[PDB]
Image (tube, rainbow, N blue to C red):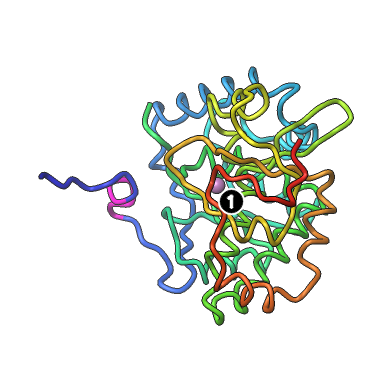
Protein backbone atom coordinates (compact mmCIF):
# COMPACT_ATOMS: atom_id res chain seq x y z
CA UNK A 1 0.00 0.00 0.00
CA UNK A 2 1.64 3.29 1.10
CA UNK A 3 5.02 4.21 -0.41
CA UNK A 4 7.25 6.58 1.54
CA UNK A 5 10.56 8.14 0.45
CA UNK A 6 13.61 6.02 1.26
CA UNK A 7 16.56 7.13 3.35
CA UNK A 8 18.65 8.12 0.31
CA UNK A 9 15.85 10.40 -0.90
CA UNK A 10 15.22 11.93 2.54
CA UNK A 11 18.87 12.58 3.31
CA UNK A 12 19.61 14.19 -0.05
CA UNK A 13 16.74 16.72 0.02
CA UNK A 14 18.14 20.11 -1.03
CA UNK A 15 21.46 18.66 -2.20
CA UNK A 16 22.84 18.06 -5.67
CA UNK A 17 25.18 15.70 -7.46
CA UNK A 18 27.20 15.69 -10.66
CA UNK A 19 25.00 14.26 -13.44
CA UNK A 20 28.07 12.42 -14.84
CA UNK A 21 30.24 11.37 -11.86
CA UNK A 22 27.68 11.67 -9.04
CA UNK A 23 29.99 13.42 -6.58
CA UNK A 24 29.13 16.28 -4.22
CA UNK A 25 31.09 18.17 -1.57
CA UNK A 26 30.61 16.35 1.76
CA UNK A 27 27.65 18.13 3.40
CA UNK A 28 29.19 18.67 6.87
CA UNK A 29 26.33 20.91 8.06
CA UNK A 30 23.89 18.04 7.65
CA UNK A 31 25.45 15.82 10.33
CA UNK A 32 23.53 16.29 13.54
CA UNK A 33 24.78 15.63 17.07
CA UNK A 34 22.79 12.39 16.80
CA UNK A 35 24.77 11.45 13.67
CA UNK A 36 28.13 11.97 15.38
CA UNK A 37 26.92 9.99 18.37
CA UNK A 38 25.63 7.17 16.12
CA UNK A 39 29.01 7.07 14.39
CA UNK A 40 30.78 6.94 17.74
CA UNK A 41 28.51 4.11 18.94
CA UNK A 42 29.07 2.00 15.80
CA UNK A 43 32.82 2.67 15.84
CA UNK A 44 33.09 1.65 19.53
CA UNK A 45 30.96 -1.48 18.93
CA UNK A 46 33.10 -2.66 16.01
CA UNK A 47 36.42 -1.83 17.68
CA UNK A 48 35.42 -4.01 20.68
CA UNK A 49 34.41 -6.97 18.59
CA UNK A 50 37.01 -6.92 15.77
CA UNK A 51 40.33 -7.70 17.51
CA UNK A 52 41.31 -11.29 16.58
CA UNK A 53 38.62 -11.28 13.87
CA UNK A 54 39.54 -8.45 11.47
CA UNK A 55 42.80 -8.88 9.61
CA UNK A 56 45.60 -6.90 11.21
CA UNK A 57 45.93 -4.55 8.20
CA UNK A 58 42.37 -3.35 8.65
CA UNK A 59 42.83 -2.24 12.26
CA UNK A 60 46.17 -0.64 11.36
CA UNK A 61 44.51 1.30 8.52
CA UNK A 62 41.98 2.81 10.93
CA UNK A 63 44.79 4.17 13.04
CA UNK A 64 47.08 5.28 10.19
CA UNK A 65 44.23 7.18 8.49
CA UNK A 66 43.20 8.69 11.85
CA UNK A 67 39.59 7.65 11.26
CA UNK A 68 37.68 9.64 13.91
CA UNK A 69 36.30 7.57 16.76
CA UNK A 70 33.92 10.27 17.96
CA UNK A 71 32.35 11.91 14.88
CA UNK A 72 31.68 11.31 11.20
CA UNK A 73 35.10 11.90 9.59
CA UNK A 74 35.94 14.91 7.45
CA UNK A 75 36.68 13.35 4.03
CA UNK A 76 39.23 16.05 3.13
CA UNK A 77 41.22 15.47 6.32
CA UNK A 78 41.22 11.69 5.74
CA UNK A 79 42.36 12.28 2.15
CA UNK A 80 45.60 13.95 3.28
CA UNK A 81 46.71 10.64 4.84
CA UNK A 82 45.26 8.35 2.17
CA UNK A 83 46.78 10.32 -0.73
CA UNK A 84 50.26 10.18 0.85
CA UNK A 85 49.98 6.40 1.41
CA UNK A 86 48.70 5.11 -1.93
CA UNK A 87 47.58 8.06 -4.06
CA UNK A 88 43.92 7.25 -3.36
CA UNK A 89 41.17 9.56 -2.21
CA UNK A 90 37.57 9.20 -1.13
CA UNK A 91 34.76 11.20 -2.79
CA UNK A 92 31.25 11.79 -1.45
CA UNK A 93 28.27 10.40 -3.35
CA UNK A 94 24.53 10.51 -2.55
CA UNK A 95 24.08 6.75 -2.23
CA UNK A 96 23.90 4.04 -4.90
CA UNK A 97 25.48 5.22 -8.17
CA UNK A 98 25.56 3.78 -11.73
CA UNK A 99 28.10 1.00 -12.30
CA UNK A 100 30.02 2.73 -15.08
CA UNK A 101 30.50 5.76 -12.80
CA UNK A 102 31.57 3.57 -9.88
CA UNK A 103 34.11 1.72 -12.03
CA UNK A 104 35.44 4.96 -13.47
CA UNK A 105 36.07 6.22 -9.94
CA UNK A 106 37.99 3.12 -8.87
CA UNK A 107 39.94 3.10 -12.16
CA UNK A 108 41.11 6.61 -11.17
CA UNK A 109 41.92 5.75 -7.52
CA UNK A 110 38.77 7.45 -6.16
CA UNK A 111 36.66 5.52 -3.72
CA UNK A 112 32.97 6.63 -3.62
CA UNK A 113 31.58 6.93 -0.08
CA UNK A 114 27.88 7.48 0.66
CA UNK A 115 27.86 10.63 2.75
CA UNK A 116 24.86 10.06 5.03
CA UNK A 117 24.52 7.89 8.11
CA UNK A 118 21.89 5.40 9.28
CA UNK A 119 19.55 6.48 12.06
CA UNK A 120 20.00 4.91 15.47
CA UNK A 121 25.42 1.07 2.58
CA UNK A 122 25.86 4.25 4.56
CA UNK A 123 28.92 6.29 5.52
CA UNK A 124 29.79 3.95 8.40
CA UNK A 125 29.79 0.91 6.14
CA UNK A 126 31.50 2.66 3.22
CA UNK A 127 34.10 4.57 5.22
CA UNK A 128 34.79 2.37 8.29
CA UNK A 129 34.23 -0.88 6.40
CA UNK A 130 35.87 -0.21 3.01
CA UNK A 131 38.48 2.52 3.36
CA UNK A 132 41.11 1.34 5.91
CA UNK A 133 42.56 -1.31 3.55
CA UNK A 134 43.18 1.34 0.84
CA UNK A 135 46.41 2.18 2.63
CA UNK A 136 47.63 -1.28 1.67
CA UNK A 137 49.30 -0.84 -1.71
CA UNK A 138 48.43 -4.37 -2.93
CA UNK A 139 44.77 -4.08 -1.98
CA UNK A 140 44.59 -0.57 -3.45
CA UNK A 141 46.07 -1.88 -6.70
CA UNK A 142 43.47 -4.67 -6.77
CA UNK A 143 40.66 -2.07 -6.52
CA UNK A 144 42.22 0.05 -9.26
CA UNK A 145 42.56 -2.98 -11.53
CA UNK A 146 38.96 -3.94 -10.73
CA UNK A 147 37.78 -0.44 -11.73
CA UNK A 148 39.78 -0.57 -14.97
CA UNK A 149 37.88 -3.71 -15.95
CA UNK A 150 34.53 -1.89 -15.99
CA UNK A 151 34.67 -0.67 -19.60
CA UNK A 152 35.28 -4.19 -20.99
CA UNK A 153 32.69 -5.75 -18.69
CA UNK A 154 30.02 -3.21 -19.59
CA UNK A 155 30.72 -3.71 -23.31
CA UNK A 156 30.17 -7.45 -22.90
CA UNK A 157 27.13 -7.38 -20.58
CA UNK A 158 29.32 -8.83 -17.83
CA UNK A 159 28.99 -6.26 -15.05
CA UNK A 160 27.10 -8.79 -12.89
CA UNK A 161 30.02 -11.23 -13.16
CA UNK A 162 32.36 -8.52 -11.81
CA UNK A 163 29.78 -7.67 -9.17
CA UNK A 164 30.06 -11.25 -7.88
CA UNK A 165 33.85 -10.93 -7.68
CA UNK A 166 33.53 -7.65 -5.75
CA UNK A 167 30.87 -9.08 -3.44
CA UNK A 168 32.88 -12.15 -2.53
CA UNK A 169 36.17 -10.25 -2.05
CA UNK A 170 35.84 -6.53 -1.22
CA UNK A 171 32.49 -6.97 0.55
CA UNK A 172 32.58 -10.49 2.13
CA UNK A 173 36.10 -11.85 1.79
CA UNK A 174 38.09 -13.80 4.37
CA UNK A 175 41.87 -14.11 4.54
CA UNK A 176 43.55 -17.10 6.06
CA UNK A 177 46.57 -16.54 8.33
CA UNK A 178 48.84 -18.72 10.46
CA UNK A 179 46.99 -17.23 13.48
CA UNK A 180 43.66 -18.39 12.06
CA UNK A 181 41.00 -17.13 9.68
CA UNK A 182 40.50 -13.36 9.55
CA UNK A 183 38.13 -10.93 7.84
CA UNK A 184 38.80 -8.37 5.13
CA UNK A 185 35.31 -7.88 3.58
CA UNK A 186 33.81 -4.46 4.35
CA UNK A 187 30.27 -5.82 4.69
CA UNK A 188 31.43 -8.12 7.51
CA UNK A 189 33.70 -5.53 9.11
CA UNK A 190 30.89 -3.03 9.62
CA UNK A 191 28.37 -5.67 10.78
CA UNK A 192 27.20 -6.29 14.36
CA UNK A 193 26.83 -10.06 14.02
CA UNK A 194 28.20 -11.35 10.73
CA UNK A 195 31.82 -11.06 12.02
CA UNK A 196 30.88 -13.61 14.67
CA UNK A 197 29.06 -16.03 12.37
CA UNK A 198 31.59 -15.90 9.53
CA UNK A 199 34.45 -17.14 11.80
CA UNK A 200 32.67 -19.07 14.56
CA UNK A 201 29.74 -20.87 12.95
CA UNK A 202 29.97 -24.33 11.38
CA UNK A 203 27.11 -23.23 9.06
CA UNK A 204 28.73 -21.28 6.21
CA UNK A 205 31.08 -22.80 3.65
CA UNK A 206 34.64 -21.42 3.63
CA UNK A 207 36.09 -22.09 0.19
CA UNK A 208 39.47 -21.17 -1.29
CA UNK A 209 39.49 -18.21 -3.67
CA UNK A 210 38.97 -19.20 -7.32
CA UNK A 211 38.25 -16.44 -9.88
CA UNK A 212 36.08 -18.41 -12.32
CA UNK A 213 34.18 -20.14 -9.54
CA UNK A 214 33.38 -16.80 -7.86
CA UNK A 215 32.28 -15.05 -11.06
CA UNK A 216 29.92 -18.04 -11.57
CA UNK A 217 28.42 -17.76 -8.04
CA UNK A 218 25.13 -16.09 -7.10
CA UNK A 219 24.79 -14.00 -3.95
CA UNK A 220 21.95 -12.51 -1.98
CA UNK A 221 21.90 -9.27 0.00
CA UNK A 222 19.16 -9.91 2.55
CA UNK A 223 20.96 -12.49 4.64
CA UNK A 224 24.33 -13.66 6.01
CA UNK A 225 26.48 -15.26 3.31
CA UNK A 226 26.18 -19.02 2.88
CA UNK A 227 29.65 -19.19 1.31
CA UNK A 228 32.77 -17.14 2.05
CA UNK A 229 35.82 -17.20 -0.20
CA UNK A 230 39.20 -17.30 1.44
CA UNK A 231 42.39 -15.74 0.09
CA UNK A 232 45.88 -16.35 1.39
CA UNK A 233 47.21 -12.86 0.54
CA UNK A 234 46.01 -9.61 -1.02
CA UNK A 235 48.54 -10.48 -3.74
CA UNK A 236 46.19 -13.33 -4.75
CA UNK A 237 43.48 -10.76 -5.54
CA UNK A 238 45.71 -8.45 -7.51
CA UNK A 239 47.20 -11.36 -9.44
CA UNK A 240 43.70 -12.66 -10.26
CA UNK A 241 43.12 -9.49 -12.35
CA UNK A 242 46.12 -10.15 -14.61
CA UNK A 243 44.53 -12.21 -17.37
CA UNK A 244 42.03 -11.22 -20.05
CA UNK A 245 38.54 -11.53 -18.51
CA UNK A 246 36.74 -11.40 -21.91
CA UNK A 247 36.92 -15.14 -22.66
CA UNK A 248 36.01 -15.90 -19.04
CA UNK A 249 32.84 -13.79 -19.32
CA UNK A 250 31.79 -15.53 -22.55
CA UNK A 251 32.36 -18.97 -21.06
CA UNK A 252 30.28 -18.08 -18.01
CA UNK A 253 27.50 -16.39 -19.98
CA UNK A 254 26.01 -19.76 -20.94
CA UNK A 255 26.68 -21.67 -17.70
CA UNK A 256 24.43 -22.39 -14.76
CA UNK A 257 25.66 -20.34 -11.82
CA UNK A 258 26.43 -21.93 -8.47
CA UNK A 259 23.79 -21.09 -5.85
CA UNK A 260 24.86 -18.97 -2.86
CA UNK A 261 24.98 -22.10 -0.69
CA UNK A 262 26.54 -24.58 -3.14
CA UNK A 263 29.88 -26.34 -2.91
CA UNK A 264 31.47 -26.89 -6.33
CA UNK A 265 33.24 -30.18 -7.19
CA UNK A 266 36.66 -28.45 -7.41
CA UNK A 267 36.46 -26.27 -4.26
CA UNK A 268 39.25 -26.30 -1.71
CA UNK A 269 36.94 -26.51 1.32
CA UNK A 270 38.48 -25.03 4.48
CO1 LIG B 1 30.11 -2.19 0.60
Is 242 contained in the magenta span? no
Q: Label 1: which residue?
A: 167
Quadrant assignment, res 196: top right
- Side of 115 relative to 262 (left or right): left
Q: Where does residue 59 sit, x and y in percent of width and height?
A: 74, 31
Query: Residue at position x 54%, y 76% from top?
Result: 154
Query: Residue at position x 42%, y 55% from top?
Result: 94
Quadrant assignment, res 45: top right
Vertical comparison of 163 with 201: above or below: below
Q: Give the position of the N terminus as an image quadrant.
A: top left
- Mark 1 secondary-structure assignment: helix
Camera-side residue: 40 or 255? Answer: 255
Q: Give the position of the C terminus as an image quadrant.
A: top right
Camera-side residue: 12 or 252? Answer: 252
Q: Which residues are magenta?
A: 9-14
Camera-side residue: 76 or 223? Answer: 223
Crowd tier of the residue under label 1, counting other residues whose Cα lies within 10 Å: few below 14, some 14–19, many 20 or above: many
- Side of 176 relative to 1 (left or right): right
Query: Residue at position x 75%, y 55% from top?
Result: 140
Q: Where does residue 39 sit, x and y in percent of width and height?
A: 50, 29
Is 13 contained in the magenta span? yes
Camera-side residue: 94 or 164? Answer: 164
Vertical comparison of 155 with 60: above or below: below
- Residue reaching furthest bottom? 155
Asked if the beta carbon under badge 1 is closer than 8 A to the nearest atom of ligand 1, the reply is no
- Residue reaching furthest top? 48
Q: Where does residue 35 sit, x and y in percent of width and height?
A: 42, 31
- Residue reaching furthest left? 1
Q: How many marks?
A: 1
Q: Where does residue 250 sit, x and y in percent of width and height?
A: 61, 77
Vertical comparison of 13 with 51: above or below: below
Query: Residue at position x 51%, y 49% from top?
Result: 219
Amino acid sequence: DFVVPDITTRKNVGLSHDANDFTLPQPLDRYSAEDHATWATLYQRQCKLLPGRACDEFLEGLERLEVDADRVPDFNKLNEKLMAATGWKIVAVPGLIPDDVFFEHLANRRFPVTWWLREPPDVFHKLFGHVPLLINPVFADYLEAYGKGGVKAKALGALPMLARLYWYTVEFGLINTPAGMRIYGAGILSSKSESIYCLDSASPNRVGFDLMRIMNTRYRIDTFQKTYFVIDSFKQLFDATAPDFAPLYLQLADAQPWGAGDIAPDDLVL
